[PDB]
Image (cartoon, rainbow, N blue to C red):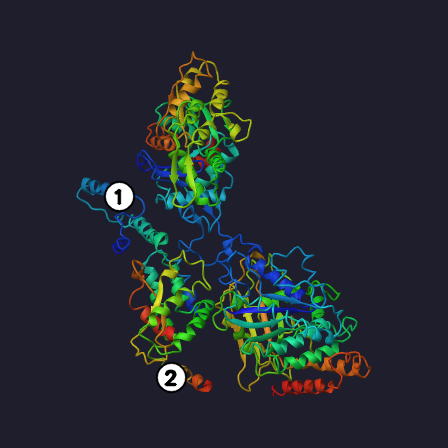
Amino acid sequence: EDDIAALVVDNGSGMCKAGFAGDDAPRAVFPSIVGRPRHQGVMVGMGQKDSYVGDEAQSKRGILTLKYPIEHGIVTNWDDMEKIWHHTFYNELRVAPEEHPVLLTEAPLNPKANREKMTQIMFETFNTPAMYVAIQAVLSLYASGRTTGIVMDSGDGVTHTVPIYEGYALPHAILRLDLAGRDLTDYLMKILTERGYSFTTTAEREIVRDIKEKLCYVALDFEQEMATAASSSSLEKSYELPDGQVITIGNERFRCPEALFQPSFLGMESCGIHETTYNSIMKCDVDIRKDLYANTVLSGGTTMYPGIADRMQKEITALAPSTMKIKIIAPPERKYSVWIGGSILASLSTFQQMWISKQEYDESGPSIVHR
Amino acid sequence: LECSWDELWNKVLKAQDLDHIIAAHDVFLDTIISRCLLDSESRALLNQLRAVFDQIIEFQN
Amino acid sequence: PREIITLQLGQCGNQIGFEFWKQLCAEHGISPEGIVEEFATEGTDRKDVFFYQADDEHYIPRAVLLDLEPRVIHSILNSPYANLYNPENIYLSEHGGGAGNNWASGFSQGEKIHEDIFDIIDREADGSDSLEGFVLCHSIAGGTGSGLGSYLLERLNDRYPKKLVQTYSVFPNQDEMSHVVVQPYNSLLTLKRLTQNADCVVVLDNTALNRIATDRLHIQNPSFSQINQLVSTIMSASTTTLRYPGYMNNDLIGLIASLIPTPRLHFLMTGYTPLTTDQSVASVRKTTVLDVMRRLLQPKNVMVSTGRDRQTNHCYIAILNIIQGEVDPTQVHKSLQRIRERKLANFIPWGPASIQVALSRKSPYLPSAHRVSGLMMANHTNISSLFERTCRQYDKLRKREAFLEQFRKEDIFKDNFDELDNSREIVQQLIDEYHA
Amino acid sequence: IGKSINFLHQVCHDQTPASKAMAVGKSAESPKDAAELFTDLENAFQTKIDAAYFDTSKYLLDVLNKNYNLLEHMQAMRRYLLLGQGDFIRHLMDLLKPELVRPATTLYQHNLTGILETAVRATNAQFDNPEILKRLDVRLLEVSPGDTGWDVFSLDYHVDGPIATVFTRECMSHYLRVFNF
């Protein structure tokens, strides 16, 4: 059919999340890496292979050098980008995309010269029968059961603030802000160094990116949360990693979500998350502004916190007018909210003539994406 | 040693079965033993490859 | 362990071992203060063959540098390199006071820096487990490299008797005699110690350097700075069985045993095809093994000059042909076939003769990975042509009265000159006699 | 195809090769044959057994490639008893000459393993993480201990698990003969 036999590949900004449609989480997600040997010899670890990719490159990362084919959300090199597509279809799924349509993703700010490029790869090399290039912004909105609103994509890529009005986005309100989650995990190592615990192993730094979502919590009003630290509150948790190095949280717990609103800890004069939210809506048409306040959606892997839903709610009124109903739609999962929207789209009734095939590709070439 | 190293190792990466791994190995491991020492027709060889084995001990001591 | 302590000595001999160490570091793909790619350990499966073991992630070469000229050891500290060199153990700060151009200078400096010269090889063999031997990397150029090399062949031969001795001797140019003027004298003194107080030598000529230097190097001038390039490559090729995986004669005393008929007949001709690399975009057709080992027995690479009239009444007996790396190495026995149909070299019917083939994997580093290299180590009995020529240069200078009293101020006071001449003629008759 | 599913039961899994799209297939087929006139398929039946065949054969080599390093052990026994690399075995054979020259003992085995582990820490250090080095031991025969010591010594590559599937009993006995020459 294609009801369960349409493949959902959500090429995110640092992890490819592949799976079959009609599920609520991806089958296999892992960070997208490739690794190129410099001199080939006798191997070590996993058996003879031309390249260690993906999850056989994440098992050995000190015998190889890591290179993301998707860097800052966008494909930098297209040769190695086919190599991770090759990895997702045949190792971390196993089906041939020639009988099964493919639903692949895009950035809300990739150039069109790039967009004809990803259409040239799937049709020729993987020889897909049909596919459709879909925005990540609209899919996360679709998992939240709306068709209009603005999604606050904060992923392992570029922060997007995309107001979509009836599946059509405003091409004069998509701000590219340079805050990424990978910027925060990196900020967190260098203020751990003020406590006296410094990294020197790449494996200890991988758990910094886990701890950021795991141990670290968000309370309302950080400013009094450091004030309650001065009267010695309970909030300081000390993770033990077997070895002498410690990753503790407590005086760096609240600074690291505070860096969402304040990029000055990172050392820049750029816009904050609420600020880049407010600048995007403040250049939108005055008649459909109301529909964007009431359909604010959090999405991405940066806003993975238990208590960031209400922090953004008590915080966003103090910018925008109060004669606006602003309601923060915060799902507990949201990394997979792009993927759950991409699977649900495969099971959409009104999508069985919005497929981009090889025959329409044969009549107009790779500008059939113009659509 | 050469003709046989380039027989096993290059064939196994062509192979897709596991039963083809033993098909490229079971033809390897019975030639290696005939061309080295023992078969049952190589007995004119290994009377001379063992007669030289003891001749270098006695030439040495 | 087969640890060798290289004994760099003389004005040309320290500089050719200087780029010998520099060649090894670039080809193992490791920093010379450090390590950066672990593709260096996956690729070279033994990097301590000629280095001290690791425990700081450094590799300290197994070298000693004494030379009577302080210029060569000053040619390290005015070079940028000095982290692959130790200023207490790999070099001392200035040896000798000698000018030098006297063989009796370096012989008395050897009998009074005698304590420090045997305290620099046991400061370079305090990590040795089992010593293979000593390679005396000396020059015959000057009285610097030639005077002191004659002392150390006696005392390493009665203090360490089951150890390898092997020298990579060079001779200075015989077409200019301003370069060293004690040259016919010092060559014949050092030859007495090589033919009964040594085992194997590898003889190398400068008039045979310039035969090749106008052939593909396109320098007419007799280099003293691009003379260290040609030498460090053919040195590192001889032990590619002992640094990269061998199989049979995986030690260097495996190769060297197999190239000696009997002593005072061991002077081996070296030939090495790729001195410069034009296989850089014409390496993609895949340079075949088949028609490139045909010159590893033809004189179109040889480092020792001889006439061409002695390549038919004198015969090679042992020739080593080292091919390296993928090249389709299962058609390599097919290459050794096409030699005999040509008779690129004539071989004695009188007892055994041998055309020896080996292979070892190539360097992890790109200019030394698809660049087919052929290492020739011949032993041809027309090697006496240099030696009769040097003897002819010896008898004429002793009748012109230079170094018959100007070399008798120290260590000779009795005539013992016709003693060196008569023994020199015993060795040359014992060579020609072997081939029938 | 029925033999191959049993070889991943020597890896032990309850997984139908790779994807779960092979599992949907069993459910689809039972109604599709049932609904038909009374007719069984059989020109199409041989078509999806190709798509099953390429799936379970590349995957049965990929389940090993993650875990056991099969073909890596194919190169491994060859350098330790088919004498593939001489720098590994000369440096063995050097350190082994003061014990093989003397009469074998009842305590012969306890020193020959120990010099064996320090042998692969005097030419090797990048194969500790590999199990090559945890899969070699000392082989001794029936030969009476009056012997010289040489002849009875041989190294053997120790095989276990689903890797002993391809390292059958008939093979290495013949390598024993070829090691000796």
What's the residue at 45%, 23% (across, down)?
A223
* Circle 1 or circle 2, nearest the eye: 2
Numbered disc 2: what chain? B
Extreme residue in the right direction: C400
Instruction: Inspect the image, locate mark 2, and give the three-letter code of the amino acid beneath it.
Output: Asn
What's the residue at 43%, 36% (across, down)?
A12
Give residue D134's position: percent from left, percent from top.
36, 60
Give residue A234's position: percent from left, percent from top.
37, 29
Q: Nearer the viewer, residue A76 or C156?
A: C156
In the figure, C264 relative to C123: above or below?
Answer: below
Give residue A257's position: percent from left, percent from top.
44, 28
Q: Which mark is residue D23?
A: 1
Extreme residue in the left direction: D38
The residue tagged 2 is B47
The residue carrying pointer 1 sits among few (fewer than 14), some (14 to 19) or many (20 or more) residues within 10 Å by Cα, namely few
Q: Nearer the viewer, residue D130 or C337?
A: D130
* Placement of the C terminus of chain A among the 4 image quadrants: top left
What's the residue at 42%, 61% (across, down)?
B10
In the figure, A297 relative to C71: above or below?
Answer: above
- The secondary structure type at the circle numbered 1 is helix
Place residue C428 in its image quadrant: bottom right
